[PDB]
């Protein structure tokens, strides 16, 4: 009759911590096979039936939203890693769940959780100091211009792909796209467009914002394509003759009235056309299509009009020119108008593409993909987003370490030899922390279809001989040096990966009970 | 959110489940492949009954809620603008690649490693097609062989009777919008239409914009030699709106007044024609019996009751402009056309508006007649294939011999290159050679012959008997060697057939998991 719980579900002690460790392995299992450039994809359907295919771990975790209390802890730390950096959320998730798996059999033996926290704090501090000593700063080294070093790092992620034959041309396209930007670099700045048909080497890079230009309507042989300082107009208005936005419907019995009805119908449209000409806007773009009648008035008044432009391309242009998108034509004025240096309409792709070159406020550019099908461009597109960040990070941070689990192996050897020198219960816990770092080089072998046993056994035995930079090659199956292969990652990013992994692992251990208030 | 009842599966069980759902689509269209393929009955959501073997129609009408099956439908959508022939053959080939891949999964081969073997073996098959290919129109422009080749593929459809007439129409249409020297053909400029009644031999090719509309008066000139085109949204008469009339009389004073506007506006709007200099008048609403009078003596043609969307179609081809109000009239907005004629079909009067440039224009539309709607609809997709074949014949003169001779010859080249690939992808190249053998094998089953017995003999003939490739006879003609039977398919259609099939197999094998929320 009278109880303390009355619907309250709570458990404490060892079974509470063990239940949380099993829940954290479910989160890591989903992003487990997505690690590596060659990792397999996933398919997530929403409640409305929309399919989503992405290999990025940060995107998958946002669509999951697991309601388990301990699962929300790793997801929140993963989102914090994606906002500050944008890569490594999979590495943080795997290391966080692997730390709990190694200490799982020790908790069932009666070991107190606070002692385990003491090991994760001590071993992490030794790993941070070891990385800073082994890190090497390579900038002007070997008297090579950064343009060539960034080129070899660009074709690294582009190697052994469908474009692997023409990748020598695409390697310079990634370098040229980054160099056009200012000291402020971000991935969402550079755009990528897909055009079906044509050879691979025909892919064009434009310093301005380009769009497909689906507009086929009237105004041919007019609207000059070369301007000096045109006023860029951004309007969502629909100028079509027959349209639902601008029209007039009036019925009467007097024939004389229909004369004023058809005239006032065009006069309402002319008032919106004259307002655009009054503001002095030269280049006039619109998201909604524009009819043939409005194009004739612009040709008579010497005005450029290009319609059917996507809104995303307008916003990338709005930031490029420095103008603003205004829905109504009455608010169009010099405040929302943009400017550009050189405008030209090219033949690229067989279809006219308009682009704004030399905008003072433009930090963005546009790269066009050319391939035989969509799968050629889609597989290449995912590789280009990673290729740009490789060029972006190498300039920002000069001190870098090798990827492919190369840095994970050196830390496992140093911490294993040091753990033997500390008498206490810390010897078994630090030793387990060293074997927990083996998950990074192991998952790269399984996702690549290789044999994880033969590679790790041959790789671990090689580090005993003193080789520091050796790691796993995702293309050929063998041990290889990732430093001479130019597989690099920033040192500060990898250091924050261990700190975020250990800090998230201590939170799950530090919780011995889950209190749920019944509602 | 909605974690309960969420589908969760992985490992080899999820891959075999995706292959099983994909083989259900391939086994469905495998029987309809070829001219002897069995038809599929279709019950529309409204209760209609349609029966056709067209592969592009089957995947469109089939609604499957399975995610992997929806990806197979998205493949045929892009192929219709490229091949249009082996659309059924790709799905059969895609199902053959996944069926052989199921055997390799039990051996422990990783799916990504399997997807690599197909891409490596695909480049060998594509390279082999260029060696065994042959040209036709190389270094010459001739319409005679272009008609004979496209006529063979059209014989399997409902156009079989008029098959000779349909081939000549597609030749002059593609040559009109595109020159054979540039070898660049735009399929969007070539339209297609249809109307019930008549026969299939009544199909006429017109260079220009064409809609079905008649003249305001029957005695108007049947052919217009001068080029003047007035495109307006209003007829020449007392003004009327563009939507609805709804005549409601008030008193007798207003009725007698309208009669004063009659005689005033009848002569005023017709004299505006001679003042501007127009001849053919195009307007949304037609003319009454009074307006046709004055147009008889001056020999001024006109078109009555023009549809709303059909107004913009004439201004694009003829180059004219739309004039919504009478104050905007002028000579610079007048259209241009070579000749405007009225062609009546048979005794029944269609009275279609025919606008021609008396030359080769950039816009052509094929207007197909026929006795049944299900025959005309099938005649539309049949001619759509001939438009795509001739498009590929002009863009690429090199062609290969169909009937299975191409898929069998590639199976021999890939099988020999397998021993040169010392790695685990060797097994993927062997399964790719056997999967190409399904297309020629499916043609033997639909023709009422032993699939295996016929297939094994043909493979021996391409080696022992003669080096050149030989095909399988589906129609039970005289003998093999389809080169004599004049069965030929385009080379680009073969390159995109195995390429689009390999791309989707690689896409399916890379998805090991599907996540959808459950209803709770």
Image (spheres, rainbow, N blue to C red):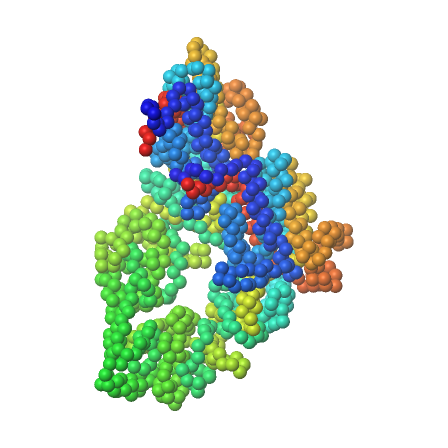
Q: Give percent across and percent down for residue B303.
A: 40, 79
* Left or right for A149, reference B164: left
Q: Nearer the viewer, residue A331 or A517?
A: A517
Q: Give percent across and percent down for residue A15.
A: 43, 22
The picture quadrant where one finds residue A16 is top left
Which residue is most to the front? A1
Q: Residue at x 66, y 53 (%)?
A: B442
Q: Residue at x 28, y 69 (%)?
A: A249
Q: Give percent across and percent down for residue B80.
A: 53, 58
Looking at the rendering, in which quadrant would you find the C terminus of chain A? top left
Which residue is most to the top? A423
Count of numbered labels shown in the rendering = 0
* Left or right for A448, reference B232: right
Q: Residue at x 64, y 59 (%)?
A: B37
Which residue is most to the bottom? B297
Q: Give percent across and percent down for residue A175.
A: 42, 41
Q: Nearer the viewer, residue A441 or A219?
A: A441
* Left or right for A333, reference A287: left
Looking at the rendering, in which quadrant would you find the N terminus of chain A? top left
Q: Nearer the viewer, residue B499 or A390?
A: B499
Q: With respect to residue A328, does A470 lie above or below?
A: above
> Is residue A291 something that shows in the picture?
yes
């Amino acid at each position: 009759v009278i109880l303390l719980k009355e619907g309250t579900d709570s458990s404490q002690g060892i079974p509470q911590l063990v239940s949380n460790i099993s829940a954290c392995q479910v989160i890591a299992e989903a992003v487990r096979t997505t690690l590596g450039p060659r990792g397999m994809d996933k398919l997530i359907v929403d409640g409305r039936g929309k399919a989503t295919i992405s290999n990025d771990g940060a995107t998958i975790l946002k669509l999951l939203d697991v309601v388990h209390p301990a699962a929300k802890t790793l997801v929140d730390i993963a989102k914090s890693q994606d906002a500050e950096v944008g890569d490594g959320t999979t590495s943080v998730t795997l290391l966080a769940a692997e730390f709990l798996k190694q200490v799982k059999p020790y908790v069932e033996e009666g070991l107190h959780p606070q002692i385990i926290i003491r090991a994760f704090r001590t071993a992490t501090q030794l790993a941070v100091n070891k990385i800073k000593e082994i890190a090497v700063t390579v900038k002007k080294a070997d008297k090579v211009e950064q343009r060539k070093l960034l080129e070899k790092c660009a074709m690294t992620a582009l190697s052994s792909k469908l474009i692997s034959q023409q990748k020598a041309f695409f390697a310079k396209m990634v370098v040229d796209a980054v160099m056009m930007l200012d000291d402020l670099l971000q991935l969402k700045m550079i755009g990528i467009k897909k055009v079906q048909g044509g050879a691979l080497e025909d892919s064009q890079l434009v310093a301005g914002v380009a769009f497909k230009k689906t507009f086929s309507y009237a105004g041919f042989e007019m609207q000059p394509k070369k301007y000096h300082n045109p006023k860029i107009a951004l309007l969502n208005v629909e100028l079509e003759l027959k349209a639902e936005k601008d029209n007039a419907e009036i019925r009467v019995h007097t024939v004389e009235d229909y004369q004023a009805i058809v005239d006032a119908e065009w006069n309402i449209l002319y008032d919106k056309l004259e307002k655009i000409h009054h503001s002095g806007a030269k280049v006039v773009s619109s998201k909604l299509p524009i009819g043939d009648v409005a194009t004739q008035y612009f040709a008579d008044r010497d005005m450029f009009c290009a319609g059917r432009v996507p809104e995303e391309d307008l916003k990338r242009t709005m930031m490029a020119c420095g103008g603003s998108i205004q829905t109504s034509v009455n608010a169009l004025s010099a405040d929302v108008l943009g400017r550009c240096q050189v405008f030209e309409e090219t033949q690229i792709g067989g279809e006219r593409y308009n682009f704004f070159t030399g905008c003072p406020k433009a930090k963005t550019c546009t790269f066009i993909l050319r391939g035989g099908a969509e799968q050629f461009m889609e597989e290449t597109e995912r590789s280009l987003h990673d290729a740009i960040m490789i060029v972006r990070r190498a300039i920002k941070n000069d001190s870098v370490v090798a990827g492919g689990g190369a840095i994970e192996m050196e830390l496992s050897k140093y911490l294993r030899d040091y753990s033997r020198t500390i008498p206490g219960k810390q010897q078994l816990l630090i030793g387990a922390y060293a074997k927990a770092l083996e998950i990074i080089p192991r998952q790269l072998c399984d996702n690549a279809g290789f044999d994880a046993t033969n590679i790790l056994n041959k790789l671990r035995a090689r580090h005993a001989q003193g080789g520091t930079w050796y790691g796993v090659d995702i293309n050929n199956e063998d041990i290889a040096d990732n430093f001479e292969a130019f597989v690099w990652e920033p040192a500060m990013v990898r250091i924050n990966a261990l700190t975020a992994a250990s800090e998230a692992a201590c939170l799950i251990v530090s919780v011995d009970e889950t209190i749920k208030n019944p509602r | 959110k909605d974690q309960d009842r969420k589908s969760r599966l992985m490992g080899l069980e999820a891959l075999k489940s995706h292959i099983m759902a994909a083989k259900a689509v391939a086994n469905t269209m495998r029987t309809s492949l070829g001219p002897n393929g069995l038809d599929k009955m279709m019950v529309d959501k409204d209760g209609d009954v349609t029966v056709t073997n067209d592969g592009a129609t089957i995947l469109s009408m089939m609604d499957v809620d399975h995610q992997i099956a929806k990806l197979m439908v998205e493949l045929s959508k892009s192929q219709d603008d490229e091949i249009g022939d082996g659309t059924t053959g790709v799905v059969v080939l895609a199902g053959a690649l996944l069926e052989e891949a199921e055997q390799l999964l039990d051996r422990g081969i990783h799916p990504i490693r399997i997807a690599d073997g197909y891409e490596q073996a695909a480049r060998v098959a594509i390279e082999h097609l260029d060696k065994i290919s042959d040209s036709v129109l190389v270094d010459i422009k001739d319409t005679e062989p272009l008609i004979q080749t496209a006529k063979t593929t059209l014989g399997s459809k409902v156009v079989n009777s008029c098959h000779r007439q349909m081939a000549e129409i597609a030749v002059n249409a593609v040559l009109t919008v595109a020159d054979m020297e540039r070898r660049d053909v735009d399929f969007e400029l070539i339209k297609v239409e249809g109307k019930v009644g008549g026969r299939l031999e009544d199909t006429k090719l017109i260079k220009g914009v064409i809609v079905d509309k008649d003249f305001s008066h029957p005695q108007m000139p049947k052919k217009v030699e001068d080029a003047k085109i007035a495109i307006l949204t209003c007829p020449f008469e007392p003004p009327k709106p563009k939507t609805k009339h709804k005549l409601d009389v008030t008193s007798v004073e207003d009725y007698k007044a309208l009669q004063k506007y009659e005689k005033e506006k009848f002569e005023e709007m017709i004299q505006q024609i001679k003042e501007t200099g127009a001849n053919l008048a195009i307007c949304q609403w037609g003319f009454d019996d009074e307006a046709n009078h004055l147009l008889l003596q001056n020999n001024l043609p006109a078109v009555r009751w023009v549809g709303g969307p059909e107004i913009e179609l004439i201004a694009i081809a003829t180059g004219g402009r739309i004039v919504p109000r009478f104050s905007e009239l002028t000579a610079e907005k007048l259209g241009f056309a070579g000749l405007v004629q009225e062609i009546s079909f048979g005794t029944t009067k269609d009275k279609m508006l025919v606008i021609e440039q008396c030359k080769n224009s950039r816009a052509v539309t094929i207007f197909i007649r026929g006795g049944n709607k299900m025959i005309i609809e099938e005649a539309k997709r049949s001619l759509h294939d001939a438009l795509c074949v001739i498009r590929n014949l002009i863009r690429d003169n090199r062609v290969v011999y169909g009937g299975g001779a191409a898929e069998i010859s590639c199976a021999l080249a890939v099988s020999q290159e397998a021993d040169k690939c010392p790695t685990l992808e060797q097994y993927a190249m062997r399964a790719f050679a056997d999967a190409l053998e399904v297309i020629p094998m499916a043609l033997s089953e639909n023709s009422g012959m032993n699939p295996i017995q016929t297939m094994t003999e043909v493979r021996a003939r391409q080696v022992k008997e003669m080096n050149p490739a030989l095909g399988i006879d589906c129609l039970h003609k005289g003998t093999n060697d389809m080169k004599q039977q004049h069965v030929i398919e385009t080379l680009i259609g073969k390159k995109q057939q195995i390429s689009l099939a390999t791309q989707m197999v690689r896409m399916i094998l890379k998805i090991d998991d599907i996540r959808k929320p459950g209803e709770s």
